[PDB]
Amino acid sequence: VSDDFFALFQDPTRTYSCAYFEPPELTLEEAQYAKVDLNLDKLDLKPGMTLLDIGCGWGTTMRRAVERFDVNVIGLTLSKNQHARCEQVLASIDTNRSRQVLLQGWEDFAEPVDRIVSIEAFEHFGHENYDDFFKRCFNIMPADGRMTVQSSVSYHPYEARGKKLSFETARFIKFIVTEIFPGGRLPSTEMMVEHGEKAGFTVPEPLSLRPHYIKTLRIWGDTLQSNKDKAIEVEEVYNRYMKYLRGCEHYFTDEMLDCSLVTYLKPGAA
Ligand SMILES: CCCCCCCCCCNCCSC[C@H]1O[C@@H](n2cnc3c(N)ncnc32)[C@H](O)[C@@H]1O
Image (cartoon, rainbow, N blue to C red; front, side, top):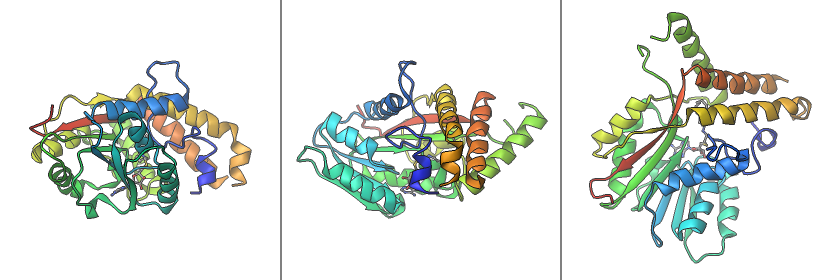
């Protein structure tokens, strides 16, 4: 997967996550900023604080946080591509706030921060590591800390929609977690909430982003579709991602997949 490839289907910001069409008539690009504001507005961010962005992408969330809230920022990513971009994105801001991006996972991060944002990185963590993740996030934050985690989710193998559809969905999901995001693994919303509660977080009712992901995958699908040619010369990979995009839209429509924005409040939050 090359940067030039994703360039032919994503908005100019290169946000590789669910957009937020509020109001409904926003551009994909506008909708990606609105999704960033949706997360940050939950975080009770005050000037001088340090915001930790876990899985920080091309640095879009962090830039918007410095600009909108007058905070310091630290970003974690496991991609050199993303790290160098973020670094130049951060260095370009007119601020005296510190900005730092580290090529490393949350597992090796242990510094005090005030607030945490994480948009669709959580699918890479592994069920096995959820307890450590939430414990780390609770422990690095002050008494009034808050964290948002946004993540696609599925449902426990038990959770009825027909035998036919449930076997089918399990397979399509295998394919995502194998050839699109190798090593990935979807949680359920219930797991997201429960592991946070066990670490001692108060967890309000999660926000479902389902119709927004449906809307996002359609624009993605449609834009890649229109570059059938331009994308092939940069056929195999093309048909793979078309199966992925059209497939997810379908299963989000069918209500076999969902996307949750979960907020985690420490006992002393405001
Ligand atoms: C609708 C689709 C259906 C659901 C399919 C599974 C979802 C796949 C996730 C796609 N969301 C993309 C957001 S970008 C992921 C970011 O998280 C980072 N990351 C991954 N693991 C860690 C980690 N352990 N620590 C810090 N950062 C991490 C990557 O470097 C990257 O910047």
